[PDB]
Image (cartoon, grey):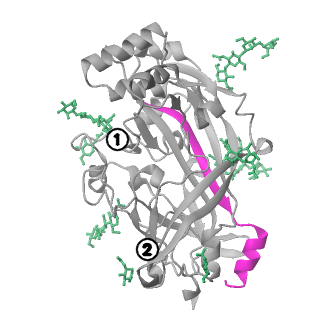
Amino acid sequence: IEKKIVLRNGTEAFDSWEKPPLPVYTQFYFFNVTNPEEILRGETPRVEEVGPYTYRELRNKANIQFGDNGTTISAVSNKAYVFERDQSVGDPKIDLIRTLNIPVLTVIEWSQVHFLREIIEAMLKAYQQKLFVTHTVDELLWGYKDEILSLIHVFRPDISPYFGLFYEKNGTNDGDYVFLTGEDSYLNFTKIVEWNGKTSLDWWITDKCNMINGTDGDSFHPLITKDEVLYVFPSDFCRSVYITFSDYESVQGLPAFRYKVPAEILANTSDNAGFCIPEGNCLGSGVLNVSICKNGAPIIMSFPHFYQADERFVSAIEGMHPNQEDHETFVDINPLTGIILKAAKRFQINIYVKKLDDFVETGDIRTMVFPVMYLNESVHIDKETASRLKSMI
Ligand SMILES: *[C@@H]1O[C@H](CO)[C@@H](O[C@@H]2O[C@H](CO)[C@@H](O[C@@H]3O[C@H](CO)[C@@H](O)[C@H](O[C@H]4O[C@H](CO)[C@@H](O)[C@H](O)[C@@H]4O[C@@H]4O[C@H](CO)[C@@H](O)[C@H](O)[C@H]4NC(C)=O)[C@@H]3O)[C@H](O)[C@H]2NC(C)=O)[C@H](O)[C@H]1NC(C)=O
Ligand SMILES: *[C@@H]1O[C@H](CO)[C@@H](O[C@@H]2O[C@H](CO)[C@@H](O[C@@H]3O[C@H](CO)[C@@H](O)[C@H](O[C@H]4O[C@H](CO)[C@@H](O)[C@H](O)[C@@H]4O)[C@@H]3O)[C@H](O)[C@H]2NC(C)=O)[C@H](O)[C@H]1NC(C)=O
Ligand SMILES: *[C@@H]1O[C@H](CO)[C@@H](O[C@@H]2O[C@H](CO)[C@@H](O[C@@H]3O[C@H](CO)[C@@H](O)[C@H](O)[C@@H]3O)[C@H](O)[C@H]2NC(C)=O)[C@H](O)[C@H]1NC(C)=O
Ligand SMILES: *[C@@H]1O[C@H](CO)[C@@H](O[C@@H]2O[C@H](CO)[C@@H](O[C@@H]3O[C@H](CO)[C@@H](O)[C@H](O)[C@@H]3O)[C@H](O)[C@H]2NC(C)=O)[C@H](O)[C@H]1NC(C)=O
Ligand SMILES: *[C@@H]1O[C@H](CO)[C@@H](O[C@@H]2O[C@H](CO)[C@@H](O)[C@H](O)[C@H]2NC(C)=O)[C@H](O)[C@H]1NC(C)=O
Ligand SMILES: *[C@@H]1O[C@H](CO)[C@@H](O)[C@H](O)[C@H]1NC(C)=O
Ligand SMILES: *[C@@H]1O[C@H](CO)[C@@H](O)[C@H](O)[C@H]1NC(C)=O
Ligand SMILES: *[C@@H]1O[C@H](CO)[C@@H](O)[C@H](O)[C@H]1NC(C)=O
């Protein structure tokens, strides 16, 4: 039986789970801001799309421990990025990007006491701080010492002087996980049952929204059916997500079902009401306020170029040209085994920006969801692992 697919010491399923043989890549694309001064005078932003900066991933399950009479398994999943110049537009240690000053907007947000806010402006004034700043791709991705934060750190040692979109993420894991192994039922293969000791999330408004559904998205139960909907808990996206069957496809020499992230996921629906922290008040279709889980930083999640989002989000920023073939999230799963043969996980990091009377640095900036960068975390099965699998398929 395809019951061969269980996380039990000695199975091939286990080994490929513990030491993933498939090479995963992350490609970074940034939006270079061309008119900072004009943006501050209330004009429409104009951005230029820079990328890729291709990094090959290094993945490994650590701290593995079995449980509940072989029903469960606990582990962490370490991810490290190795830069590939040959596959990139340029050197991230040289190439520059003018974008928003996330540390300053992050600090302005954190302040809701007048004294606190008076202190911050004083520092911005004195230090001649700006809303639009230029850094290397490397500094933006991996971290740079910020002047304002360095000074805050002196008074509040809990506050880090460093900032990066992926700061302290090279080598680390996304917390402790306890997975249900396919021993009790195959449908229950790699199903997440706990994340950081909690069986559910606590940062959303409704019981439904806070649910931890599905697998980490790196695998799925065997014997899938064209009609079922598949759930994924992408830790980074801060909520569970489901994917729906699109069509049949052939990867290497193996059959697959093309599963895509449907529009409904981030649409302004009743089932997505609880993803709106201001007492139900929603920003709009195609965007997620990930502020609660991003330690108060004004981060807004979306899909690249605001694909599957409200037209107003696209009109807002000049240089946004969404399309399905370039911005969608798909995954080609071999139906029999549940093994991902080809995939593309694509999402965008945005900042919620607006004119603040207390902060001259904002000027007359339009109230908007500002694009910073998006990525393409992708996978493609190799001829060696594919041939190995054809024996089973
Ligand atoms: C991670 O995700 C990103 C997307 O966010 C990917 O990057 C994109 O890669 C696309 C291809 O995968 C790029 O799209 C191309 O852009 C070209 C112009 O910039 C355009 O010319 C290309 O069009 C051809 O391909 C289409 C199919 O996709 C065809 O329908 C079309 O007619 C074109 O056909 C070619 O041209 C003639 C006419 O038929 C033929 O003689 C050729 O043989 C045809 N070739 C092929 C292969 O069909 C296409 O739209 C896009 O530029 C790029 N964008 C960015 C920002 O990077 C990453 O690739 C992705 N995955 C990985 C693993 O990297
Ligand atoms: C993202 O957008 C930003 C802003 O537009 C952009 O940054 C700019 O990059 C250019 C280089 O591409 C920088 O220009 C240099 O500036 C220094 C002085 O500050 C000059 O000495 C340099 O002079 C050279 O110019 C020519 C070669 O480029 C030669 O003819 C000449 O002899 C010199 O060698 C050069 O002008 C500029 O400093 C930045 N601007 C800012 C705000 O930092 C960035 O490159 C864009 N990113 C991408 C990847 O497109
Ligand atoms: C996490 O997972 C649960 C279960 O997988 C999700 O809840 C499920 O949501 C669907 C629709 O929101 C419910 O189905 C409904 O069935 C009725 C009856 O046929 C139909 O009228 C509706 O149109 C709809 O199809 C389903 O009952 C419900 N199940 C449970 C156990 O709650 C939940 O939404 C997911 N949460 C996240 C954040 O992904
Ligand atoms: C994105 O989510 C954040 C929360 O993560 C939203 O911020 C919250 O905004 C509300 C207003 O709708 C703030 O509530 C009020 O705050 C004052 C000051 O403390 C208080 O006296 C009032 O009684 C009320 O609670 C709330 O403080 C704030 N939450 C946090 C944690 O900062 C934000 O509005 C969302 N962004 C967008 C663009 O919608
Ligand atoms: C992320 O961490 C990894 C592991 O420390 C880095 O990759 C290796 O480590 C050193 C870095 O100087 C070098 O031997 C090679 O670059 C890598 N070797 C192997 C065998 O992987 C990686 O460079 C770090 N990435 C970033 C973005 O800093
Ligand atoms: C698998 O095999 C033996 C069972 O005696 C055990 O010592 C070993 O540590 C197990 N492997 C893992 C990764 O736990
Ligand atoms: C996993 O699934 C099987 C049947 O689908 C069931 O017996 C088992 O209790 C499941 N666990 C949970 C908590 O859903
Ligand atoms: C979202 O939908 C609800 C009704 O379903 C509506 O009250 C709300 O204003 C809509 N959000 C936006 C941003 O228009």
Is residue 231 in view? no
Image quadrant where residue 32 sits: top right
The residue that disc 2 covers is: 228
Residue 55 higher or lower than 384, as above or below? above
Q: Which residue is drawn at 60% across and 37% down?
A: 142
Relative horizontal placement of residue 19, taking residue 223 as reference (left or right): right
Tell me if 281 is positioned left or right of 64 in this view.
Answer: left
Name the mark on residue 106.
none
The spot of residue 59 in percent (x, y) is 64, 59
In the displayed structure, 289 sits above or below 97; it is: below
- Of residues 326 and 374, the one drawn nearer to the viewer in this rendering: 374
Could you tell me residue 129's position as x and y percent? 48, 14
Q: Earlier in the sequence, mark 1 or mark 2?
A: 2
How packed is label 1: few (under 14 Cα within 10 Å), some, or many (20 or more)?
some
Over which residues does the magenta segment extend? 369-393
For the residue marked with disc 2, what is the amino acid? Glu
Label 2 crowding class (10 Å Cα cut-off): few <14, some 14-19, many 20+?
Answer: few
Residue that extends furthest to the right in the rendered view of this protein: 86
Secondary structure type for disc 1 = loop
Most distant residue in the top direction: 126
Quadrant of res 64: bottom right
Residue 374 located within the stretch drawn in magenta: yes
* Quadrant including the N terminus: bottom right
Q: What element carries label 2?
A: loop
Could you tell me residue 78's position as x and y percent? 58, 57
Query: Residue at 54% of width from left, 78% of height from top?
Result: 7
Residue 284: mark: 1
Residue 173, given in percent of the width and then of the height, sits at 53, 54
Q: Would the CB of label 1 be found within 8 Å of ligand 8?
A: yes
Q: Quadrant of residue 139?
A: top right
